[PDB]
Length: 130
Ligand SMILES: O=C(O)c1cc(Oc2ccccc2)c(OCC(F)(F)F)nc1C(F)(F)F
Image 1 (cartoon, rainbow, N blue to C red):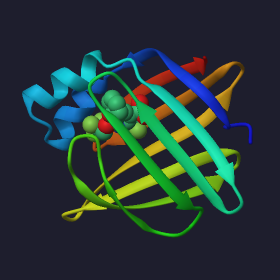
Image 2 (cartoon, protein in one colour; image 1 turned 60 degrees about the vertical axis):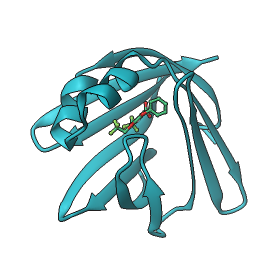
Image 3 (cartoon, rainbow, N blue to C red; image 1 turned 90 degrees about the horizontal axis):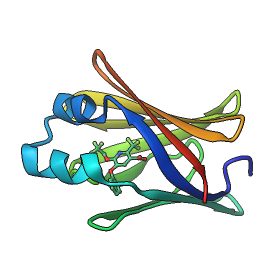
Image 4 (cartoon, rainbow, N blue to C red; image 1 turned 90 degrees about the vertical axis):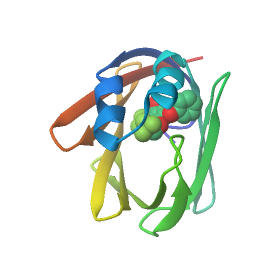
């Protein structure tokens, strides 16, 4: 929809702190930090697919809005994820071991803005069309 497309990471703030707050170890944070992924968002019927592709790591999720699904994250957490659309924002929550983190995806001007929150840490990542 407004989200559909092939997006390239152009800026990131506080991603290392965000991964640290999630408990990600040094090697995986290193890989993640200097990744510059593409994010490819598509929709077919009820099903949204978000692929995140980079030289050292790829992930993919497919989901129906409002329906919980299992996910293995890029940092290898096994989580229960639910994604909803709220005022134009795709809101993802991941739940595991009594914790949660939120990842909000929104469209702003030419940007796909990704805000990731874990406890007191807020990370902002910005994608632009490829
Ligand atoms: O889409 C993102 O840019 C993104 C990318 C992530 O990791 C990568 C890095 C390279 C390739 C594919 C995935 C990631 O990992 C979970 C983490 F951060 F906990 F490790 N989380 C996110 C986000 F939080 F924002 F959704």
